[PDB]
Amino acid sequence: SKNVVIYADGVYDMLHLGHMKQLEQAKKLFENTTLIVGVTSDNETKLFKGQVVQTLEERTETLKHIRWVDEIISPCPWVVTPEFLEKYKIDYVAHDIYAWLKRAGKFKATQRTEGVSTTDLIVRILKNYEDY
Amino acid sequence: SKNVVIYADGVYDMLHLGHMKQLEQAKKLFENTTLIVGVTSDNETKLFKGQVVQTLEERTETLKHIRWVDEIISPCPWVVTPEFLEKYKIDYVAHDIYAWLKRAGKFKATQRTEGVSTTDLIVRILKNYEDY
């Protein structure tokens, strides 16, 4: 009956059924939650992880439309820290380097789904043109 | 203060920021609404309109995740009829052949947004490879 504050962060480029399944998961970890979602900046994402198709603005505007999302932090810090949790009253971090979080009892796992990615769909479109 | 029942239908292939902006629109036509969304079957869509990338199941599972959607009719009739409105207690149809609806005062317009389409994004990805 107590409202539990959950935080998940990510890039959320080209949001697809896989991200939304993950968010729904985070959001339903408990009966009553506030799901806060953090969206990584363009600068840091490109430099530390890989290429990004959509700007911060775009990746964040799409998340506004997902029913599980209660609040958004955009851009979000690239590294989560104890101070960040305190600042936002976050009870758990939902994700799939996490050591410190598990240690603190503040880590809750979520899963991915395969073959649901937007890149996979372009694949499917192209099958319509046999190789010969 | 009265709950107004809105119906929008469509294909919703590869749901993108343009569909969601449209749904949010339908959903906020009034202060209190129930937004019902109808998802066209694979058979009829392909035969009457054009190619579809995602199955009925997929296009409908994605819509479940959009915050504006209150109920889904999947598959939905390809043609809306007076009987259909009565059956589901629909006050207005939100869309962008509609004659009969306007005549009845049961038609409410919504808009599209350009350049937000998933196909546009593959375009953007490809610019990363100059033509020479």
Image: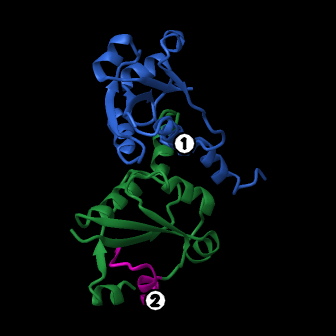
Chain colours: A blue, B green
Q: What residue is disc 1 on?
A: A21
- In the image, residue A3 lies in the stretch drawn in magenta: no
Name the residue located 44 percent from the left edge and 22 percent from the top edge. Answer: A46
SS of the residue at dot 1? helix
Nearer the observer, B101 or B27: B27
- Magenta stretch: residue B87 in it? yes
Count the marks. Answer: 2
Cβ atoms at labels 2 and 1 below 8 Å apart: no
Q: Position of residue A120 (x, y in %)?
A: 63, 44
Front residue of B105 and B35? B35
Mark 2 residue crowding within 10 angstroms, few (<14) / some (14–19) / many (20+): few
Identify the residue at image location x=51%, y=23%: A50
The kind of residue tagged 2 is Glu
Q: Which mark is residue B83?
A: 2
| Quarter of the figure that contains the N terminus of chain A | top left
Residues shaded magenta: B80-94
